[PDB]
Image (cartoon, rainbow, N blue to C red):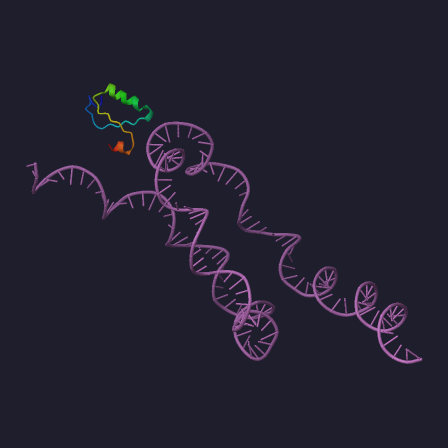
Length: 49
DNA sequence: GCCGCCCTGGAGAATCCCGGTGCCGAGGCCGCTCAATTGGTCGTAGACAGCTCTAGCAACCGCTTAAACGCACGTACGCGCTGTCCCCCGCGTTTTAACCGCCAAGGGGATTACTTCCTAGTCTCCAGGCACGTGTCAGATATATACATCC
């Protein structure tokens, strides 16, 4: 609603526990498929990528 | 008949043991004598209580990730053996100086007692240096925007 209706499509940050991480990823992939949701874990090289 | 040679007995001297007496090491006793003891007084060091704030601790969690661990291989090094030669050890001989016992006088230093005075302890008062907190300021850093240029 913030991205589409109010045109606030800027950078948003969501900080979640690691154990609940796929439960947010599938929710983003299902409910809002047009969003540019990105993932941030890994070692130093994955985060550099 | 006279002279020379072999066998055996008792008295004189050396040695072991015991008693009386004098000398070395140590302990009891006495005398000085100074430092430990006793008794009293008082100040304060520390024990105790109380409140506040911070670190540690037992037992659990979760995540990351680098260190630890296990294994295989290979090769370098510890170790054993042998040779060799050289240098240290044992011994005999000669020297030499350490060691002990001596001057010869003089100064250094340890005590005992005494005198004196300078300097450091102690007390009171005060002030500024140290510890803590904060406003402000100049150097370092990151980016906004305008100009020259290659394809």
